Length: 190
Image (cartoon, rainbow, N blue to C red; front, top):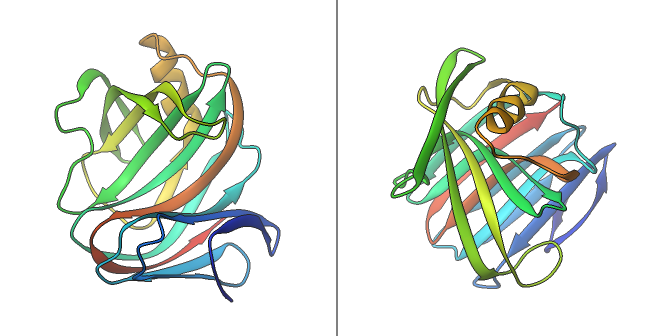
């Protein structure tokens, strides 16, 4: 059904939905690992289904449609603790490539495309453990798509090889993020 921000389990999948309270976003949990999000002149939000906790060798499958009109991403998104890391495996995006101005730390080939690896830092920003300063690891797919399979191990290994280590895994989901834009998406995870 439609719901307001929060987290929980839906049809055997962990889900997380958050927004800054600006309005213009509708998140709906569907059957199984399906979820849909429709937004129009939204604020910042993140929504998706996955696992809690994630694993370092999970093969994530996603199928759907993703139609952003503006700034938005479609990625495998999650966190690690000790060290605190926010990571992204970006499969598609809108008007803004999140790696813009970021430091490139390598390339990895996985699931039909080459990905560029980057590391950024967030200073005194909200996190799963409260306001903090932490790094962000990114894997940005060159060939964009809204369906496919993601072998997380290939990314986590490549990151480690470059010196980008991860700690204990927290949640791991396939999420749609938007930043003051419009769009629609319907994705099924498995």
